[PDB]
Amino acid sequence: EEEITPVDILLQLVQMGKVDPWNIDIVDLTEKYIERLREMKELDLRVSARAILAASILVRMKSEALLYAPLRRVERYYTFDDLLDALMDALEEA
């Protein structure tokens, strides 16, 4: 296409040992995602719309996590495959 996708940013956070794939803190993960998203945009690299929309979703998922330990089972800690499904489900219904 070729654009930075939401998975690209999440995998590089995992691969560089910045998050634990088995216990992800959605509150701590959200700003790490935004940090990396700001890095790509500083270099003016192509970042997809889904990667931009995923930031808004992660901000909501971290706000509800802080308010609850809604209209869903609000979790604070995710696994990587669970967060991937949770984020992609929110991306496609957005």
Image: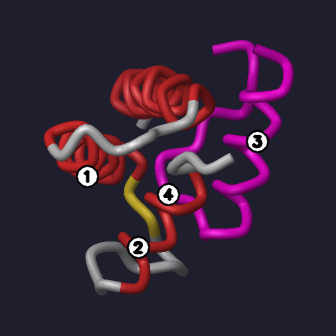
Identity of the residue furthest to the front in this view: 1
Q: Which residue is mark 4?
A: 77
Q: Position of residue 88 (x, y in %)?
A: 76, 42
Judge whether 38 appears above or below 39 on screen: above
Horizontal side, residue 42 vs residue 40: left or right: left
State which quarter of the image contains the C terminus. Answer: top right
Question: What amino acid type should be assigned to the residue bearing mark 3?
Answer: Met
The mark closer to the camera, 4 or 1, is: 1
Judge whether 12 appears above or below 94 on screen: below
Label 4 element class: strand
In space, the residues marked 4 and 1 are separated at their CA atoms by 20 Å
Q: Around disc 1, counting alpha carbons within 10 Å, would you say few (fewer than 14), some (14 to 19), or many (20 or more)?
A: some
Q: Position of residue 89 (x, y in %)?
A: 82, 36
Q: Which one is earlier in the sequence, the residue at label 2 or at label 3?
A: 2
In space, the residues marked 3 and 1 are separated at their CA atoms by 19 Å
Q: Which residue is mark 1?
A: 36
The mark closer to the camera, 2 or 3, is: 2
Residue 69: name its quadrant.
top left
Dots 2, 1 in contact, CB < 8 A: yes
Q: Position of residue 87 (x, y in %)?
A: 67, 41
Residue at image point 25% right, 52% down: 36
Q: Around disc 4, counting alpha carbons within 10 Å, would you say few (fewer than 14), some (14 to 19), or many (20 or more)?
A: some
Q: Which one is earlier in the sequence, the residue at label 2 or at label 4?
A: 2
Dots 4, 1 in contact, CB < 8 A: no
Task: Find out whether residue 11 is within the magenta segment.
Answer: no
Residue at image point 74% right, 14% down: 71
Q: Which residues are magenta?
A: 70-94
Q: Around disc 3, counting alpha carbons within 10 Å, would you say few (fewer than 14), some (14 to 19), or many (20 or more)?
A: some
Question: What amino acid type should be assigned to the residue bearing mark 4?
Answer: Tyr
